Image (tube, rainbow, N blue to C red; front, side, top):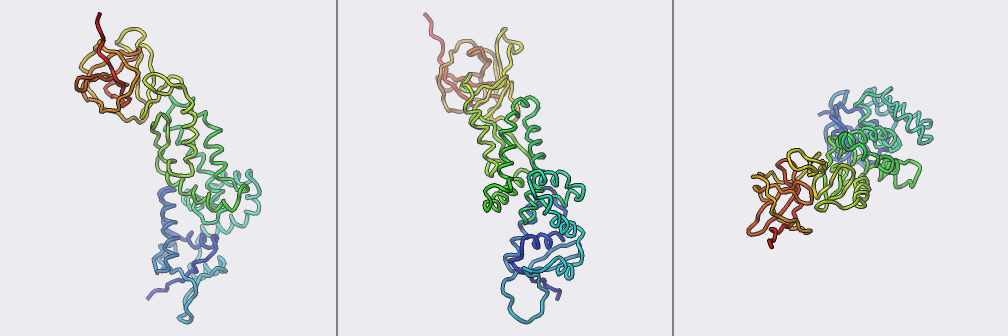
Length: 359
């Protein structure tokens, strides 16, 4: 017969934040934090009793609207203060710092630059866990400021994923991340939209809290994790630069020492060892789809037609040097085909071949 704290479903974001910030939960990363705060906000709206593990022990809460009169309960209303809260829950050291951050917003939220400086410096007052909760706060003005820190982390993981080999490319930098995050995080611009842009951005920072995976699709690099988020537009602008890139051997896109086929990126290497001088080949980089094959030996009795097949790569074949490149070549019924090859990996950009005609 414990006390069930009745908490008004309409409580303001800041109050909601202070209540939630009693949580004992130790958040794994932004994904976990986001998951935990989302469950809790949902629980509150169901208006069903449910549990709340705090740093003052376990309480039970229940979201309400109009309170049925009588059975004197303890109630957190829309107009309650930190004080009313502390009367019920005790003191949360975190909540108190949060009351403090709010108090100083009148300074740090003045402009982009104040917002950035409060963000960058934030760990001077909060530890990693409390930071992550700030980054999922309901109060827009706090979450938007705190999230600023995540751009740096995410930007970084992006380069790392792209490896050294692709650093030159990163120089999609400014027109990138920078502006996209900027637009997405902007606090003064098209407001009233802000509540929604901020909620999309939490979702998106959750989506990629955990890892960043670069793949190749349709001859573009794409960051899987931005794919169904408001951060897609970075995948889009990258696609657009790939789009405009020059077409090359077997229908790939050329940039630098690299080639970008349907579903994989390879570096082109001049004079691949162990073939004639001037023979070129391919070396897969990063994540590739293709077919593990067997190369029985070299044959030179084929010509590459300018023309695609859209058929299964056979798992045993030969190498053949076509258009100056070491390719994989296979037979399929009476017909021949060629494909890009790296080591014993065949990519699926299948082109038709003809056996040579004699005089």
